[PDB]
Image: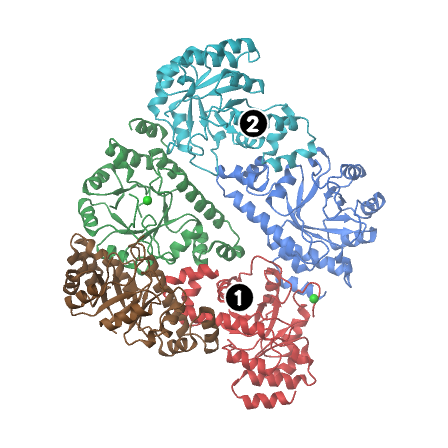
Chain colours: A red, B blue, C cyan, D green, E brown
Amino acid sequence: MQKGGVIMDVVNAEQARIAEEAGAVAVMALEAAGGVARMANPKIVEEVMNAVSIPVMAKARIGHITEARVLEAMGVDYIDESEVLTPADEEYHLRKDQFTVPFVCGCRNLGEAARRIGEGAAMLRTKGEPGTGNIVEAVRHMRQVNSEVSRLTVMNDDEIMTFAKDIGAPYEILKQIKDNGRLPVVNFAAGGVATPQDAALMMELGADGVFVGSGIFKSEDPEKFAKAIVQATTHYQDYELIGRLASEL
Amino acid sequence: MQKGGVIMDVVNAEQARIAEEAGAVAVMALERAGGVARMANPKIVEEVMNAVSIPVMAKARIGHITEARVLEAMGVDYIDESEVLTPADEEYHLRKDQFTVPFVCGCRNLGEAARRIGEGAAMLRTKGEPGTGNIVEAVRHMRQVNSEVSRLTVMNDDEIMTFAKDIGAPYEILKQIKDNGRLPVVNFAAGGVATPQDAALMMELGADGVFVGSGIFKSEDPEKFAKAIVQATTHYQDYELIGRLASEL
Amino acid sequence: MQKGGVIMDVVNAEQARIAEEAGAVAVMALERAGGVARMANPKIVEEVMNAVSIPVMAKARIGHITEARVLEAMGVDYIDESEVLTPADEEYHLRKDQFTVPFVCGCRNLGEAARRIGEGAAMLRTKGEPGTGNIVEAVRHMRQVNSEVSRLTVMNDDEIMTFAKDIGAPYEILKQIKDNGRLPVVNFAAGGVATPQDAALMMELGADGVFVGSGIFKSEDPEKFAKAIVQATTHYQDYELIGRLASEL
Amino acid sequence: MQKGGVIMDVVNAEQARIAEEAGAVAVMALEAAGGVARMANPKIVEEVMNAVSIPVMAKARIGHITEARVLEAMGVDYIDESEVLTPADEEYHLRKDQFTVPFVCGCRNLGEAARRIGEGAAMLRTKGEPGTGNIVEAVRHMRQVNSEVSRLTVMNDDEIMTFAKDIGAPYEILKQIKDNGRLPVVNFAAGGVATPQDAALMMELGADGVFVGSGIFKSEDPEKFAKAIVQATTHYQDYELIGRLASEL
Amino acid sequence: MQKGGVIMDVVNAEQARIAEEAGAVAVMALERAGGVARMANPKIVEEVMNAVSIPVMAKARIGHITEARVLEAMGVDYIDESEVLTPADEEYHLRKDQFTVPFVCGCRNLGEAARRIGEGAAMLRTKGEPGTGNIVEAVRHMRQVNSEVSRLTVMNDDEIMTFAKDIGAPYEILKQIKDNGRLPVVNFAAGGVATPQDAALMMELGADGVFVGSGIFKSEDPEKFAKAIVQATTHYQDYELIGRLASEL
Ligand SMILES: [Cl-]
Ligand SMILES: [Cl-]
């Protein structure tokens, strides 16, 4: 879809323009801790869409059918059934396959990833620890999903079903993963990316892109931090450029 | 009995008038950690009744026979044996069949629903989490009741009795539910409805109506907010109209 | 329905004739650690029916619809869904209301009694400890049912529902028991009756009749023993006659 | 496949001929308690196949690839990955989809049934308690599978995935069951069928046929018992004929 | 090192000759609740060596340095530090790298396999359940080792050390296994092989050979049975030939 890029969380049109100028592959509209966290007001989403030409994403509460249907009616590119917001259903997720708009979901293991894909998700990402600035949770989630997938690619067929039963995964999804040799969708790194070295590390661990952001607007030079993150996600093994960019922050 | 409507909590005559002008099917008279919560003063109920022509409802403490009989003598349309008030009897509910006025009660599963119906309740609603603005508990209760009813409609006869024994439901009530194919009374959504998307979501889950709290008057434009809630409860699948209405809140 | 009588377990035509001559109100056809206990062969039931003019009863495994339907097609008077046989369904009993022949079931408390009645049982009896000769369990079950019924007859209405919820009884059945002032069906004593004093004691506790096992034919004079059991079940307070009859055993 | 019939376990050519004369839809070749229970000698299977024209089945140890491949090379119609035999793999079942011969497996719940179907089973049956003559286990397994399937046919889509996760079932199998309205394969009753009334009961509970046998050869008139079981499996609601046939055993 | 062969347990010269005539790649000298199991008498080992030209193996107690050194001085080809004998050291195994003769050891997982290899073992085999005739434990051990090796071959480098730390394996041994892509020594199947189908199944699971116990001589035709075992271990996918050979046993 949009592999190799950086996704930023914007709060107005100015931050969206700064993101487009920095080289972000997509934007995420959002309005922070306390109370109930619901979807953003449609005016903010419409402003974010009118501000940039890059695809704009919006978050919806888990299991909230109406929020996702409203974001779909608005013409949003992708919808993020985000656990960042206060969930709406603590038992059942959205049946994203019944939707026209593609969906991105969070996961921490191959079981969660397979359950989200079977529910109709088009894109995946790590849950991480959003708002903490700590990359350890995203690292753990990425490494767990990748190790389980590597096991599944070289697992004996006779042992696949049991494996699913042990991790709560749909059998057909695991068979598809084994036949294709990798995840059928892209898996991004989200929650915890604070420095461009964090984005480079997540891309070195085998991520298909960086999803976290929001904090880039808090720096003394927000545009500089955004450009540094975007340039560190791409060509993540050029350490000299990474150090040079980090020196100017 | 008047399914598909919106019921609002009012505290004075002005709120009752505003709710009537918004298009609410009925009103609920209320007074206000909060100490002991009892029934409202009869003067406030009389004011609410004289303010609007729509049916007026009043809350009574659980198991408080005298409060309910007084509200019946006052001429209220429906009485809510509401757990939101400090209960008066923590072991037995009132014998609603021995009353002349209809009753609405809260429930979280088919067992509680059947226990309330067997006692003579004329209406049901989810308990939810009142005052929290989170529709999680209402969603959970509605889904649980709907799932147990779906079980009961297509269940073998030999397995009905034990089912009642396992859920504390009256046997004849469960047999009637199986024979009719649905609940004998309407089931509304209550506690947690914060946005028009929440009302549309509760109606999408199969509710027969929504109960709005006092937060509807907390908006900058309470009249517009109440109108949006009403217009979203009706035609709950028109997601474009829901998004348009929410853009103005 | 024929209250105050004695029911005897017979295995052939001679035993049925001897029980008829003793004055038993009905007979029970039987075949025999004992492996699996199923219904008796239809030939033995037909022999028992052709041997005596009194009503003949046959036992069926719990939840075994086919055994009960076969016994109904054979023309049996009553069917005993007896736990003394190896049960066929350990979760659900047969829907006795959907049958044409009346049923007698075992019970140890008002909850089991009400569950059996709600399923359509026409008669009740204590489970006891069959084959032990000890009337302890029959006494216990009879006293428990009588105590719970005495509670229910003089209990407040508001406390009925919870009571059902606490004992697994159908609400309408408990309401009917409260309104009528007694059990809707007769309750017999079964399992443990060894001496005529045991039958007189079960009748003193408020039973509507006694079920005699196979030990009645184990005496040196089986006819005299059966006659003593019958003469003690009737006029159970004539202690001098009971002692006289027991002196000859 | 072969719905409505009775399957018998034969040990030689004479019992297979008696089964074919009785009206069995298929035969099961077998050679009993103690030690290790493996597949039968190929000579016995070849004799059973040469004795009758009805399809012949053979049992293989669970997870034993070579035993099933040998039975497939022999030209056996169906293979029974039977838990009756001492298992060969206590973790992983055979991938029956990779086979040409159709497979029949045992199950006790919708989870096991879905795991067996996803593994490539063409036919199902209850595990029961083989060799005990007690129908209670088959009754429990049949009722559990049927109740879970009835739930699944009327379950909300948004709740399906979670349901699978709760029972360890493949998501696609459950979706297929919901879309078709029933199990995609036939579900037979096995283990415990001792009397023709047991077969009639299993068919009244919603089974697609009777699978248990073996014991029919132990009666005084084995041919008579076999004919009675075959006639009771078909037209299971003719209770008069069932009683007549049972009277002659 | 001589992969794909069959190793047989012999007790005299006649058994060694019969095993050689059957086509076994090597022989195992043995003597016999059974008290204490020690190494065999040197006279029996010398007899077995003089009887056949194939390589002869002898078992030694675990950690018994002197037994192994004596067997080395006797001129044995391979030594089996077999747990089937009563161990002499329950804490430490012998330093096989300090010996001149090659060693074969038992294992149940990659941890035990790596611990044995690091100590200098030249060959591996499953522990199984010797004397039971049940291939369950051999299947389990083989599948566990194969699964852990499949994990290790496609595992990230950063995750290797911890993996060793979590399984008690030497780090350099695991690195060598990852670099070579397979085990550094052959892994045989042992303990539980009862039928030629069992040998074919162990070879299908990826074993490098089978260890036959003493039951091969318990058949009515021991020579035919041993020939069938050998002919099934080789070309283990020719299921028609396996069935034909088994038909004669
Ligand atoms: Cl917070
Ligand atoms: Cl045994």
- Say if E149 sits above or below A167 in the image: below
The residue positioned 67% from the left and 65% from the top of the image is A37
The x and y percentages for residue A19 are: 63, 81
Corner quadrant of residue D68: bottom left
Name the chain under label 1: A
Q: Dot 2, how many residues are within 10 Å of its Cα: few (below 14), some (14-19), or many (20+)?
A: some
Q: Is residue C20 found left or right of A215 in the rendered image?
A: left
- Of C99 and B161, nearer the camera is B161
Q: Secondary structure at mark 2?
A: helix
Q: Mark 1 = which residue?
A: A100
Q: Position of residue E70 (x, y in %)?
A: 27, 70
User: Is the residue at mark 2 from the same chain as the one at mark 1?
Assistant: no
Query: From the viewer's perspective, is residue E126 above or below residue C142?
Result: below
**How busy is the neighbourhood of tag 1: few (under 14 within 10 Å), some, or many (20 plus)?**
few
Q: CA distance from mark 2 to mark 1?
A: 67 Å
User: Quick check: can you spot residue A134?
Assistant: yes
Residue D186 image position (x, y, % from top left): 36, 48
Residue under numbered circle 2: C140
**Res E76 seen here:** no
Check the residue under mark 2 and report the chain it is in: C
- Kind of residue at badge 2: Arg
Q: Residue at x 36, y 36 (%)?
A: D198
Image disc number at residue C203: none
Q: Which residue is at a point 38% across and 18% down the rendered structure image? A: C49
Residue A220 occupies quadrant: bottom right
SS class of the residue under badge 1? Answer: loop
Q: Are marks 2 and 1 in contact (CB under 8 Å)?
A: no
**Whereabouts is ligand 2, in terms of quadrant?**
top left
Quadrant containing the C terminus of chain C is: top left
Q: Which residue, as the protein is rendered here, is positioned at the far right?
A: B43
